[PDB]
Amino acid sequence: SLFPSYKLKIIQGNELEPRAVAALRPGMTKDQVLLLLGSPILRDAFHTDRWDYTFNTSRNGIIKERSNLTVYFENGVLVRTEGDALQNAAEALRAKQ
Amino acid sequence: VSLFPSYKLKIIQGNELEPRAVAALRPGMTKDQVLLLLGSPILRDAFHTDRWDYTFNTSRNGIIKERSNLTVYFENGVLVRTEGDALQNAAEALRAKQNADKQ
Amino acid sequence: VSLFPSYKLKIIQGNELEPRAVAALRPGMTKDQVLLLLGSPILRDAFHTDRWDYTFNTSRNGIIKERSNLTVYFENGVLVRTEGDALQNAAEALRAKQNADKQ
Amino acid sequence: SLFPSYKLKIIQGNELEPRAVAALRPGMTKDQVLLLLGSPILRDAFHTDRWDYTFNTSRNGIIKERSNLTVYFENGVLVRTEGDALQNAAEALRAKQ
Ligand SMILES: [Zn+2]
Ligand SMILES: [Zn+2]
């Protein structure tokens, strides 16, 4: 064969919950974000005030995108968020309407 | 740059524990090598992240019986360390398959 | 969430102009639909970018004869506008194929 | 067939030039970045001081990653850079050594 052939496994899990992501607001305590999103995987020193999440995004039975989310804290409350998951959840809810 | 005009790709979507794959991990493996062996973890950019985390399922009769976690660490682009109970659960499943060959 | 346990994927790597594909663009197409028709543009995250830019090549006898640019715009997740000389170059190639059928 | 089958085209072009990306330094004029990287595609008002680039990253004949680069300017000189391409070029040169 002139063209190669490979087998790739895409890990399933942590499907994006748009309502949970679109629920984050500045001023929420760390405990609030835990109740909304669950604990992140990393919990070292550098990630005490920076929590990383990664979600799977599926459409029509296919995993299409890994959507990342970062939550920043100061004095135990949420100060800002960034990542693809924010837009991913916003447009997912707007498409559901 | 030289590129294949086309290639074929079979995708598996799941998180079932693959004992033989986990048991084949070796120090010095590249990130490309680990990806083809264990699968693409739930990371936006695995190529440029030095720690990957997996959560595997062990199911029998269609029921998840236990969950196994695996963490792989990379330094200078090669594998150097592993953590998580997926390592021991994989070794126990391989040895259980051996004991069953001997009845 | 319901997922296919596995699916097959044939990948084409190139930037050759595909006249029929360009000529099949319609208003209202989703981003998933445009991706399967024209290809995945050189964008990190096309799903969440509202403008995509393509640069196509027209080659004959293995020599790039001209380059065609295409820009697609999305609003509310569907296609609404196109720019670039790939549109006219694709229409001219399709009509040239027709004229050749008539000798 | 129980499993679907799809055809996907991955667009070739704009291959990452690690030396060019690793050459960017604060204080370079816009003209310098043009000579190093060429012009970006977007050139509207919002992108007068923010230039976006995207590159293909290939290994062993396969396109593996689309690597993005953003260059920020103030008073016509480069102030900072961000994107995957920076790490992508750094580790590509370190692996070439
Ligand atoms: Zn990367
Ligand atoms: Zn996205």
Image: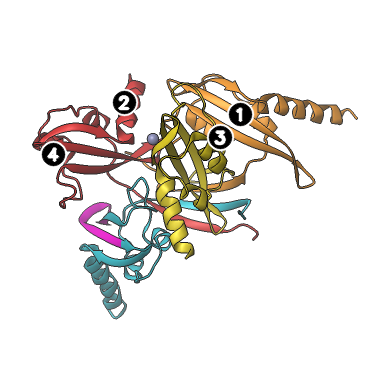
Chain colours: A red, B cyan, C orange, D yellow
Q: Are marks 4 and 3 in contact (CB under 8 Å)?
A: no
Q: Are marks 1 and 4 in contact (CB under 8 Å)?
A: no
Chain bearing mark 2: A
Residue type of the residue flagged with mark 3: Ser
Mark 1–mark 3 distance (CA, rounded to whole Å): 17 Å
Crowd rating for badge 4 (residues with CA inside 10 Å; few <14, some 14–19, many 20+):
few
Asked which quadrant contains residue B30, the reply is bottom left
Residue type of the residue flagged with mark 2: Ala
Tell me: is circle 3 under 8 Å from ligand 1. no
Q: How would you classify the magenta stretch by its main secondary structure? A: strand
Taking B67 as reference, is D75 left or right? Answer: right
Q: Are marks 2 and 1 on the same chain?
A: no
Name the quarter where the N terminus of chain B is drawn: bottom right
Chain bearing mark 1: C
Chain bearing mark 3: D
Mark 2–mark 1 distance (CA, rounded to whole Å): 28 Å
Crowd rating for badge 2 (residues with CA inside 10 Å; few <14, some 14–19, many 20+):
some
Q: Hey, which residue is sitting farthest bottom in the picture?
A: B102
Say which residue label 4 marks: A34
Residue type of the residue flagged with mark 1: Leu
Mark 3–mark 2 distance (CA, rounded to whole Å): 32 Å
Q: Are marks 1 and 4 on the same chain?
A: no
Say which residue label 2 marks: A90
Say which residue label 1 marks: C70
Q: Position of residue C58 (x, y in %)?
A: 72, 38
Say which residue label 3 marks: D39
Front in this rendered view, residue C94 or B76:
B76
Q: Residue at x 52, y 39 (%)?
A: D32
Q: Which residues are magenta?
A: B56-73
Element assignment for label 3: loop
| Lower sequence index among marks 4 and 2 | 4
Element assignment for label 4: helix
